[PDB]
Length: 255
Length: 215
Image 1 (cartoon, rainbow over the protein chains, first blue to last red):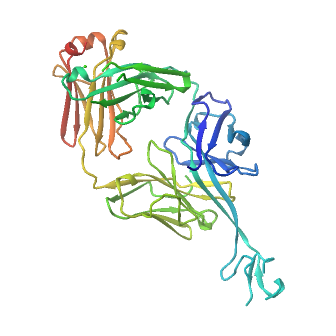
Image 2: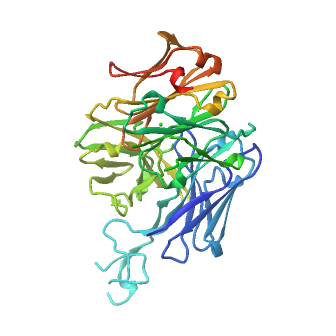
Image 3: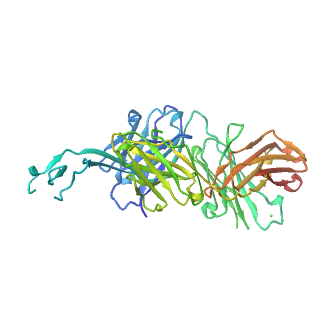
């Protein structure tokens, strides 16, 4: 399979710049999907931003309306979100999503809707060849919203802080126990800013036995994290830091 | 968060647990309530729409109901996998405007204890060429998610320049943490051994490295 959603855009934006994200939708059986945007700030709940439906109608969180803009290019199955004059409070994980949005006709108790006698009435009873015979009332309108499929999320930091590219050091546990049946290899991703980094091994050929640990904020004011793999073959850790446009593929000597 | 949920719920493996979601006549009271599951290091997943309908590929252990302004999510046969944050949601005043609950962290009790696996890395040659030496102590597959890390050089306890992460839940509901000891290269080379000592539920795993065998 069904729809897959990929957010793309910058991981770092300065205060009072415009934040622009793209959502790419692939694998829908359908010509077009209603697409919405949700964010989660660290240690807060989910917050609705807005959506654009298959007719190009936009709806926004009325708190953020004056700051938000959602456009679509159906030629490239893309939806975009612009958020103007961002501050550090706009730091969050941004998700795009497919949304279901529908208005239902709501009839009071003991009243039928539909054309299964009557068709020309919202809510009716025959308590009947023509509509004037039935006992009727006007519908109320109930609003239905829900997210069908979620994206992966994109981490956005709003900060004046400078970027620092990581230094990548190769790690071996070997000298701990040189007769060990297995060897544990790793990479130290040292002194970077901001989050995130992505770490793979052998360009994603080596997935099983991989453990990437959460970043620590060190006393330097910079992040570090480590990734390790246990193996009983060259070994390379692939480290991407999107904020600095840097990739490092580090050779790790295995004992 | 606008809709009210308990911040915490606990149940034991195989038992039943319920999460409530309270709003007003203008959101939850209209129905078409939805529920979302967020397992950490992961994208949210839709569980329930239209008060009671399970989403595609959600198991029948998950069920929901609404009574006026209060929606309830019920998880039967609790598994370790069900540890997550759960959120309810509703349209508010239009189908393109939505409010979320404050979120509930579900804890699943009666999981088996799991001692940490500990790996201690010495400093890389490349780092030592810069007169810095970072010792890295990697701690994984422990339950529950509480460890204390002590570093030793030649029987001395080291407290200066130690940075230990919080424990974070892996996807398998066990925990990981890391400790970093930042030295100069002189400090590294001037000692017979450095040790990472990890205590978990009164038990201690110690790994040791010797500069003499690692440089």
